[PDB]
Image (cartoon, each protein chain N blue to C red):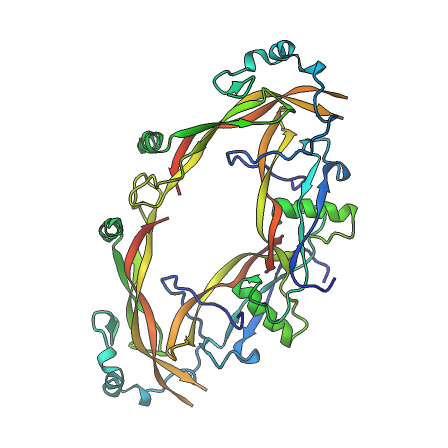
Length: 140
Length: 140
Length: 105
Length: 105
């Protein structure tokens, strides 16, 4: 039952907290991009990653995809992630997407990317799922 | 500051609670419709009362008034009120009023009617404001 | 009263609180109230927030941190006849007046 | 601690609660917690519901009725790296984790 907290499918993702420390941080030797790129391999998505810093339900869908497009902005994830830079998506909650004005653009469908994570107790890289946005819904 | 509870402009109106009792109830003699009608007088609104049981902001308005009309249903107020029957309004929260579907019809503007109320400590009729609905907004 | 978090009865008589001078009707209503313990663990039948869960575990390891509190998690409104600031006796709705459900926060 | 309803500090270390077996990161976070008295009257600076106001007055006339409780009235979320049911280490958001404000309920 209530053994532990319950997660949430809300996006985008709140920045993960981290107190850095050359110990909770990789150490160069274990940073060989050649060997890193191989450990990720097919999971590397160049369209969203960078080594260095750069019935009627159909009508709702076609509509939202027109007025609620996903906006992407490169985001730095820190040193404990590889790749270090990930293009993150967000919805355009500026002007109202409906008529009469009232609704706004909200995420409706996510997509899981796989990237490397540096974890310690001793220490090493591991793969994790990083969710990003692929569709925005015009909801309220 | 927080001396007492704070009211609310939300409509329609929750039925007022009352434990009846021939004592908290008028007594015929003080029921002469001839004298009652005179005590109310100009406040009597026949369109809503019955002696016996029967820029862009403009666009939002014209729209809501078209798809969010006020629906009226006669409502019995009991014996401690005069007149006893009052046409109450409500919004059509059945089908969605916006596109893409998401918003619904919600009240946006009220109107105060004046009717008689039988109150005791000794006992007599008094006038009170009874709010009704006159406009519905297509909001969410 | 060591039972778990649940709703308890409670009728409020306005004249007993000195509100009959501005509230014309009703003479009072059933407001209820929440009470009971928020224990470790929080059973399935308990409405609780992630923080209440987190805080409850902390209380199990450190008694210095208090347990989550049993408060209303669902309320309803009531209409009231009363005299306003302008000296007119009005009839309006009052939200968050009647406790409908209890939970741990 | 007889102060009024306010937010207090509280860092939760997952390993101290036995959560470091499923939570990969972070090692813990600042959850805070609410505490303090909800007195009569409830000052301007106190977020309170109509029922809390009603219940507070009842407590002033009848000590058998408890005062309103000081609980979180505003919370925020945090992301967490953890292992899911399918054995995949996922990164998701967790709502109602950090107490942002306190009030009387």
